[PDB]
Amino acid sequence: AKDPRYVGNLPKIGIRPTIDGRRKGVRESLEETTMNMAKAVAKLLEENVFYYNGQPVECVIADTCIGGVKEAAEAAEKFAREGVGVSITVTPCWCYGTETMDMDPHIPKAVWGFNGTERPGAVYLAAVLAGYNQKGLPAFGIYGKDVQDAGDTNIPEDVKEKLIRFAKAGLAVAMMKGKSYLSIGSVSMGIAGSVVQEDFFQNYLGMRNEYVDMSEFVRRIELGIYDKEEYERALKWVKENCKVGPDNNRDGFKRTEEQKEKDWEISVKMALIARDLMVGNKKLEEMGYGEEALGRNAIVAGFQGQRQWTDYFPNGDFMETILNSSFDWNGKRAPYIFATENDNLNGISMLFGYLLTNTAQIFADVRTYWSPEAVKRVTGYTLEGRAANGIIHLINSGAAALDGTGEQTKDGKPVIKPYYELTDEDIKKCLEATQFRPASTEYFRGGGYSTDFLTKGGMPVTISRLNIVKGLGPVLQIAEGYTVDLPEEVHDVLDKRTDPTWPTTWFVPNLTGEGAFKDVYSVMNNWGANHCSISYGHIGADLITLASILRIPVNMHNVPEEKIFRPDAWSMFGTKDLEGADYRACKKL
Amino acid sequence: AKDPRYVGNLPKIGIRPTIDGRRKGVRESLEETTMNMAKAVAKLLEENVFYYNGQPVECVIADTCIGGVKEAAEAAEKFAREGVGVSITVTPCWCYGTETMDMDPHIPKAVWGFNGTERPGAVYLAAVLAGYNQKGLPAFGIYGKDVQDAGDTNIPEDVKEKLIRFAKAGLAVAMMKGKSYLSIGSVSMGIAGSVVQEDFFQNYLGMRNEYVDMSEFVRRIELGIYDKEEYERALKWVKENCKVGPDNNRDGFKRTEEQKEKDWEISVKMALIARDLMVGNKKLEEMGYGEEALGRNAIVAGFQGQRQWTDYFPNGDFMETILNSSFDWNGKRAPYIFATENDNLNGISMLFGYLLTNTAQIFADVRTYWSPEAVKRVTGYTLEGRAANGIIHLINSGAAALDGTGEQTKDGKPVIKPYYELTDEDIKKCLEATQFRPASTEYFRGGGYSTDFLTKGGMPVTISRLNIVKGLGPVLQIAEGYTVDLPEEVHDVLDKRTDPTWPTTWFVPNLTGEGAFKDVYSVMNNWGANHCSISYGHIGADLITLASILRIPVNMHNVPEEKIFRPDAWSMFGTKDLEGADYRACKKL
Amino acid sequence: AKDPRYVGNLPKIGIRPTIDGRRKGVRESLEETTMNMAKAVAKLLEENVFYYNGQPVECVIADTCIGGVKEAAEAAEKFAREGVGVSITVTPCWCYGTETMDMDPHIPKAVWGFNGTERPGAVYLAAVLAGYNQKGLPAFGIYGKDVQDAGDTNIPEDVKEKLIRFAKAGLAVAMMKGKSYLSIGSVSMGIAGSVVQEDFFQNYLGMRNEYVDMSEFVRRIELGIYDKEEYERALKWVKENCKVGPDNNRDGFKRTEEQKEKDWEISVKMALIARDLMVGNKKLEEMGYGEEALGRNAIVAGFQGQRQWTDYFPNGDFMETILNSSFDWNGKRAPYIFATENDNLNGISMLFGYLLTNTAQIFADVRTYWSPEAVKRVTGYTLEGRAANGIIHLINSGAAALDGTGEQTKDGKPVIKPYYELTDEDIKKCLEATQFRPASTEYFRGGGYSTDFLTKGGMPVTISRLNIVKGLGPVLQIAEGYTVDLPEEVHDVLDKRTDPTWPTTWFVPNLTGEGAFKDVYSVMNNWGANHCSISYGHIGADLITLASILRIPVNMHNVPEEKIFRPDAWSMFGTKDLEGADYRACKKL
Ligand SMILES: [Mn+2]
Ligand SMILES: [Mn+2]
Ligand SMILES: [Mn+2]
Ligand SMILES: [Mn+2]
Ligand SMILES: [Mn+2]
Ligand SMILES: [Mn+2]
């Protein structure tokens, strides 16, 4: 399938049916069963893994079973021509290891060996994995716990989970290759994550780095380099659906009625310009701006904003809010991963979660750790339930996807859904639960509008953050948990003394009693940056698998160890201490 | 303050109050609060951290709050000009990360972010730490667990503990820079730690290595190159305060009355010469020995002794005992860290504890592990209380600070206090509990006097040892515990069959039931050398912090995990296995 | 002396007079001669090395001769308090190597041993250098070729050259530490050198990295955040001294009279804003812009310009031209090193040359290699003299210091002089030889004015370029040579078919017949970037010494090998192939 926004086609998954090369009876008796395995996996993935636009992932099966190097080469050739970016080998029998291996170092790969007795399928799995480990080509091993009878095409639940987790992680990795990260502006207020380290994007993600000074926005606004007809529709949509909340600026800092109207007009134009920069716009070509019409083929981007832009122009809160949302004046759509303060590392943190879920991601500041003692002192209220041991205030500096309201619903529960599953009611409620507040001029002299909402509680979420550390390189931290509800009056008190015009999410991380998860305080004390990305659901296991494919160690996570799924080679670096083995594997491999 | 013994001034602690650069609002409303925060830290440190001579540590505060690079540069300039060797950044608000950072890679640094709600102080803390981690400049992060109201001048207990631990560790590290280790003699009886590895002193401690052959003592004794007036006073003092115990040498090995008198005279001259070599002596100038008067500016030194010196001259027991003590014929004073058998690694182990506590350190041999079974077999006594699981006999080859008697008392408990807190009674009791015994001529042919005492039990102590391992470099081991009392009859039996003319300390390490602390046997079986250093108190956490500043991994320690305080970067190398992360961080950073 | 533009004081040079520690006659007889050596060096440097503002460098001599570690520590202490950033040890006798060494790893250091016979001065030089080499502390060795009689205070010419070369290089290195590189804008048109690699600035130069989006210029222009009184004086000065040349834009691309006037006004404001950003401006504080008044303490900066800024606003040609010049509407002054296209690596290339000469540096594109064959075909003229083997066209995209005209004169020859040596005539002639041309709108849509001049021929110059290569890090290339004159009609033809509105310098590199200097073509074919920096004079030897102090290998240079002066340690890595030894030394040390 053609990628609807970026150059090229969406990555496909190649299935390699390996077989015993011996004829005279052996191979002849196994071709049908082997191909059936390949077809079963293709069916499973097509029903469980989808591209960001909702289309089911597409699979490519080798033209013949693979019993030797000639057929292995043929599969490699077909996969290269078909645009395969992930490979899965399947077999119910013994096959000749190195002769049948996928030797492409640039493709995530897994091997599923049927747990049958008639033929040495597990023997092949273990044999070929030894080969992948010996040759330095990381590969995932999938072995079902229960013996299945010959010919059984039903895929066991444990096998299904691994195939799907591998496929999603593999697809996410394949998705980033060749795409750009667009840096709009430069470093924002000395934030480390806004410094662009090209080596990371190039060598770990296979991405390109593009740059554009914020003065580009001045030019496009002044010369009207954007779809004027869309602009008018957008402004109208905003006036009808975006409710303006109270102005907290005290008289001396309040902007005039005229300024506030201009703040909206420019805020909308900023949204159009940012999107046009990321994916281009044919309309610009028709207007006589052919170069600008091309776009920067960016699957993720960031906007510096403070201090230079915001000291004079409306801030990027609205732009950053709307782009990351799953809808706007043009209807429901996939989000455009966009980082506040040009924090490219948070942008990538968001991108990882997005590519694994197809859901909008929430950019946030790890603002305050509220202990039970502190909440009791300040409000007189004793935290209860999930919040009993403390909570963490997640709140970005004025911008957050409207999906963050938690108003979208599934089975009577709060969630964030892929845009293609949204109902008109879901969207309507997200908007109703949001208030747009005139920006605090003491911080944002140029005005603008911040996003004010409160995430509904009880929603499972995962916060994560990618950091780059000297002497180590990229490193990922993860914290699965839940959003919580506080009594209205309690929230109001904690909220008012912090930043009531910004978006709030009350978070409680799952505790393990060990490491950085002994208590809630420790989770925040061990967070390596001032920002994090929030995704709906518990995607820690998926992030761990994705990280291992990228050779990015995970310094902190609260995912049950039984759910850790990494390439087989990792176990060769240690089975007692998985964390240490992870660092050793990422460094050597 | 001027260092009373070494070149230059004592290290100062610089306080950097960082602030939001935005004026016409934010900055003006935070100027007083931020500067007051800095002043509060200075006050706290001045009341809890003291130089080795008892003077309160001196702090330097930036002339203005730091909101950008210009002010950061001005703070760096002022700090360099005023002799700052440790820095602490403080703030209650958001500040511009890299623009406000302390970029001096040569000084220990910490950042304390106020846990307040009104401004993003914790956001700055995490943001700047991400910067320190990204740039490879280790920095400690201090974040209080309970939200405090704006302007709260009171520093919470958890924050206080971190500020003080960091300050003490940083000051100790700063104290060593530029000072010398003086090797008197060469390798002693093939002891690995008596081999001097200049790279360690130079690159890890910033120290210089000086050398002087023991023949220097022959020249100074023969030519009278020492303060003769002091010598006469010292001899008189020894005769009046140093009690001579029974001679255990049997006929043939017993020295004459004349020899024993000369042994005392030479032993005292040795003490004077050793001290003169370490810090110089202005008196030598008028005597016509100007070069010798200078000294070697050594904050630590060692004396080979066996086998060359002791095969003919009185041993170094008295010299090694007196220098390390907190008092002598000239009154109470700071110890002169001096290593027996020129074991420079034990000398540094002692120096670490000394610089962190200002208390005399005990040099000791890890002589015998006494299991409950062994004690029962040999004495018929069943070890009780803290000693119930076994004890370790710590006893140097004849020398130990008189402070080791444990006669010094505070609140009715045995301790070792900084010399400036000593009472006349403390000193008298230390001397009364000590007996000087004629050295065993089978070992020490030249005679001398060994120190015989028994450390009082119930005193919290910490033993430690620095080792240098090929392929790793320096590595530190720590064991907190207590001294114990044994029934007199039991002690006598164990003592008589070991070395009753030497100083005894019965030690029991705290057990954790894990690692090398599963049992008392394991603690000794895992000790990496024949020597260790004993400090009063449980200073393991302090030592761990100091080790991390020095990038020296800790291979073994029984400090509760919750008390481990290392630079923020360490967590980036692992949160589940702190030991592994420590090795990874020390090597890469 | 106080640095007139940056925080702190200008670096001082410390002189360490080492001596034999032996009294009884030796030391007593040498103190006078040893101190006399120290004084002689101080005098020599004060008369030959000057700070960028023309003030003579300041030296600090140790309070006593250094015969041991105590005195060495005293010198280190005095130097630290006096602001010493470069050290030179001097002695006419034998001294105790490691006991007298300068152990500061962060200070460039040299040792001058008197070539006398009475005392082993050369023995000390060789002995201590062996120590510096063994300890990994690079130090330069200075030994005169001719034996001098005892007490001779005259410094031989060969010794003088090394002392001065070391001092200038050392001072240049000391000058950069603690200063900022200010990035104005982001990457310019995918130019590699405009990507900022913080690790380079931090670890090699000890510099800070500051960032500001070009939108800052929009704000300051719109809100009048600059000295309006100076602005008026500047505009008047421009109208009176900057002659406007012909407009080459063809009708359809010509800007109106009104636009051209605005182009001048904005171009001038850009100059003021850029300078204010680099060093601050007290006037801004008086105007109510206290934060902006501070500046970014930048000793070098860059402006992205194309494509974002220039697509709408007047280009940075005038700003980049005037800042780099040695004069403007406020009179003669030190240049402000400013990089076109935010090429920070060319900015540093320029900074190296500037700090070694105090003269304005020329930013240029290595545009065209003109072979004799090509010139003959295109013009019918046969290149003569120095140009006989071909020439290289150096011409930046519209900006160049007016000093580049070569109109400044000394002894009837064309030169570029430090601003403090300029005569009114020199300045007047630089302006008269320059024409400001309306910018080519096909490239610069926002207009502006390019600098059009022709560098006078016969001037000795050195072009250089710093590049950062993956797997190597920073690497420097140098090409000494001369500017040449072409017959007027010949220049006109080559010029008109290239870019006649930009500044031209015709360059001929000195050839060696080997390496990258076998012919003129090879010099350009081996240039590692599209830009270079031009400095008056043959400063290749100075750049080589500076590079070795910074541990930056020199991949290409045409400096006679007899003039190569690097730390003594370099010879330990090879004496046959100096280039290979350079790479080996820079990597290991
Ligand atoms: Mn933020
Ligand atoms: Mn709200
Ligand atoms: Mn011993
Ligand atoms: Mn005893
Ligand atoms: Mn150019
Ligand atoms: Mn011209």
Image (cartoon, coloured by chain):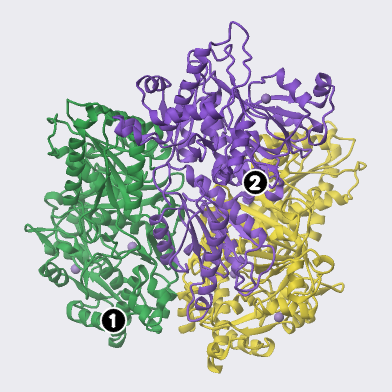
Chain colours: A yellow, B purple, C green
On the image, the x and y values in percent for residue C446 come to: 36, 78
Nearer-the-camera pick, B319 or C80? B319
Q: Which residue is mark 2?
A: B541
Give the position of the C terminus of chain A as an image quadrant: top right
Looking at the rendered structure, the kind of residue marked 2 is Ala
Q: Chain of mark 1?
A: C
Q: Which residue is mark 1?
A: C231
Identify the secondary structure beneath mark 1.
helix
Q: Is residue A343 above or below residue B170?
A: below
Q: Is residue B499 above or below residue A177?
A: above
Task: Give the mark toward the camera: 1 or 2.
Answer: 2
Q: Quadrant of residue A173?
A: bottom right
Identify the secondary structure beneath mark 2.
helix
Q: Is residue B467 left or right of residue A76?
A: left
Q: Residue at x 17, y 25 (%)?
A: C118
Q: Quadrant of residue C348?
A: bottom left
